[PDB]
Structures are given as structure tokens and as C-alpha cells.
Image 1: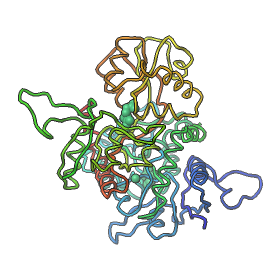
Image 2: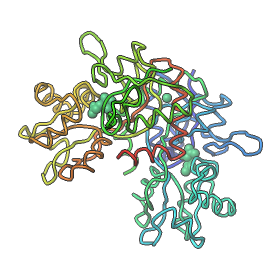
Image 3: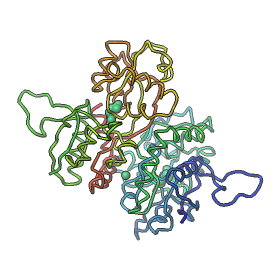
Image 4: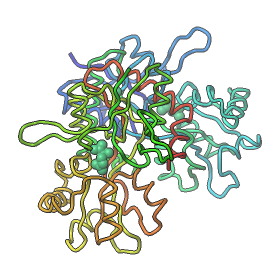
Length: 250
Length: 248
Ligand SMILES: N[C@@H](CCC(=O)O)C(=O)O
Ligand SMILES: N[C@@H](CCC(=O)O)C(=O)O
Ligand SMILES: [Cl-]
């Protein structure tokens, strides 16, 4: 049977392809992760059906009831066979689902405007005039929520107390906030690179705050995890992932 | 106790300097030894460090399929873990298991400053400046297998001059860059260490590829996923970053 592949809209990894005519099935989608999925299928010999995650979330565990949401929950429940998306490999996720080895490496950083006095997370933490936030229920939010580092702990205190006003539903919403208000957005460096190649007034501020990879997610125990790792290693070595990066980040 | 295979390579693993003779695990220090210590704390194992007898990382013989180096030790179940700057590669992942990466890197070029050489392509299209890599490591294996024109050409050069331009260790390659007209293909993490200590040397060009170092285990080992979890803990705690800062 075809594998069910959960994913999420996120430029330039996954987007709706443009056409003057209606599009159907997998042909509706394009992006770096869609190219990745196609190449994985070429190597491993599977067929697949792409399905956008219904709640539009990456995945986090609820504080109170300990339930997961997003693509992570879809894998846990065996509603999908793979998640092919910019899904960060994290400690808490690795406890409940499996991941291939990373196809891309990245870290949290800051998206803000050029020409300002802000040069680091510490600069943001030490003030309140410039608001800042992150995507709700993603790995970046979770990093701040759990950090014992003073600077990041202070930042979580600020974001948490202003949740409704500074946390956003999507990277797109965050980027828009940066473009239209005095706001700095905590987000992943890979995605910042895409944004700053298109928006010449924006820049990454400071360096990477952490390091992590994106991996293909599978339900815990899936035999596809190790096969997908081997295929990713092949695509990396052949230079195909690099060409895909160049294609989509232009 | 676990048997841990490793290899001498600054600043990942080195012999501690000391006045008094050292024994057993006390003999060793470095980034990978700190990593091993952190992993043993999280997972609750004790261990014996043993340097790989043949001094090799691991490659497969093109004729008879035999492996050497730390990879061989894992295949033969002579070691439980390999904790070293051991690159996760396609060919190795088919025969051993690896944790997720504790460090990310890529092949690049080590050479002297002040020249017009700016890329692998610049090296490939000439012969005056010789170039090479560590024998029986991941970098050599990348070139050997590459379908990319420039890299295929570089493999043709290197293999035809194997006895002169391929070296036994990074240390030997670095000395060769310092004493002759030679550019060394080597891993970017190690280049960073070298260029922070040798102001006449520099990385040429960017990364030629992308890979990680992982803890190796025999195929099917229960330790692989446990070590991955521990590495993720260490990354998220900020310890992997502090470990790199310490040794670099
Ligand atoms: N890629 C992230 C979502 C975006 C973010 O948290 O910055 C994740 O896997 O949760
Ligand atoms: N770290 C490499 C050895 C050095 C190199 O090939 O540049 C390996 O795992 O084989
Ligand atoms: Cl893995």
C-alpha cells in the first residue's frame, strides 16, 4: 500500500504549487521536502499520499493532560507512516516517535531588522520595548519553556506572560509581525536564511542559540526509519540535498 | 563493562601529558573522552578504552569486502562502542549502527593563506600543488565513490599518486601542508582546530559535503538508540557546545 505522509505548509519546504488549472493529489505540492520525499521514494521504492496535518501544528505535549498534537500526534496514533517536513529532532520527541538521521542541520536564532542596536538574545531579554516571540507548539517554544539558562529563562517569562500577543501560529505570521511592527522573531536558522534572501531589510541577529537537525519522523519502531536514514545519506553524498537546498533557497 | 574503541586524533582523543606513568582509562583525554564520560553518567555503564590496533578509521577493501579500523572492530563485535570522530556515512551505515550526530561538519581544504586557490575546482585543474587525504577514511572514500566530475578528477589524481599524496593521519597531512606545496582534504571541524593554532593556514572554499560524527555500535545494538537519546540531552543542555569550546 501507499505510505501516508503527513506534512505542514512551510515555505520553502512545503507549499501549494501554482497552476492555472486545478491540481490534485501529490501534484498539489512542491518544495524542498516534497523533492526530498520524491527522491526517497525513488531510492526505496514506495508509493505515497501526502496529507497536510489537520491541526496545522508541528507537535508539542500538553502540560496538563500529557497529550501530543501536530504531526507528532499523527505518527503516535499511526495515522501517518512518515512525517516529511522541517520537523526538529528533539529529546522529548525522540521519546515517543522515531526519526531518521538529519537531512538538514540548523539552530534557533533571531529574525529582526537591519541597522538596530540589538545584537543578541541578551539584548532582547534585557528590555521590553521590542516585543519578541516564537511559533506556538513548536521546538523553539519548547526550548525556551525548558531552558535553565538565565537569559532564555527571562525570555520565556516575557513570552509566557504575553502569550496571546507575542506567540504566533506559524512562521509566516511571525515573519509578518517582524515586517509590520517592532518585533523580533525567534525561529530556525534555515528558515531565516530563506527569509533574508527575499526580504533585504531583515537579518539574522546574533549566532545560533542551539543546534539540531530536521529528520523524517516515523511511528516508534517503524522499519522505515533506518531505510530512510540510508537513503538520506546517499542523497547527501551524491550532492542531491545540496542542489535541492540551492533550488529552494534562491 | 563496555569495550570502547577509539583512535588518537587531536583534540578528540589524546594521551594526557604527565610526570607520572598513567594506566588504563587515565591515559586519555579530549573532546571524545569527555563525551564518553558524559554518556557513561547518563546511561550508567562502565568502560575500558582501547585504541584501535591498526590505527585506522575504517574502509572496505574493494576486492574481498573486508573492513579495517574501528568499523571492523564493531563488525567483529570486538568493541561495544566506537567513541571517536567517526563519520556517519552511507557505506558504514550499511554495516554498523550509529547514534545521531554529536557534531556536524564537512570535507573542506586546508592550505596556506595568500594564494589564488579558492575551491576544489582550482586544485583539480592543476598539478603543481599536490593534494591528498587520509588513507582509509571517509574523505578518501567520498572522492573514490563520487560521480561529480571535479571530484572524480581529484580521485584520479590522488589514487594515481597514492603512495605520495595519501597520508596515514591528519597530523601527517597538516605537516605536509606546512612543509611543502600541498593542500589537504580534511574535515572542517579539524581544520578549525588547526587554523586557530597556525595563523599561516586557512580553510579554502566552503564545505564540499555535509556529514556528522556519531557513536558507532555493532549493527542491531540496543545501545544505539540509548546513546542517541543521551546525545540529544547533552545538546539541549548546552554541554556539547561547552565541550567543543573547551577543546577547540
Ligand atoms: N520546525 C519546528 C517548528 C518551528 C519552530 O519551532 O521554530 C518544529 O519542528 O517544531
Ligand atoms: N573522520 C574520518 C577520518 C578523517 C578523514 O577521512 O578526513 C573518518 O571517520 O573516516
Ligand atoms: Cl538513528
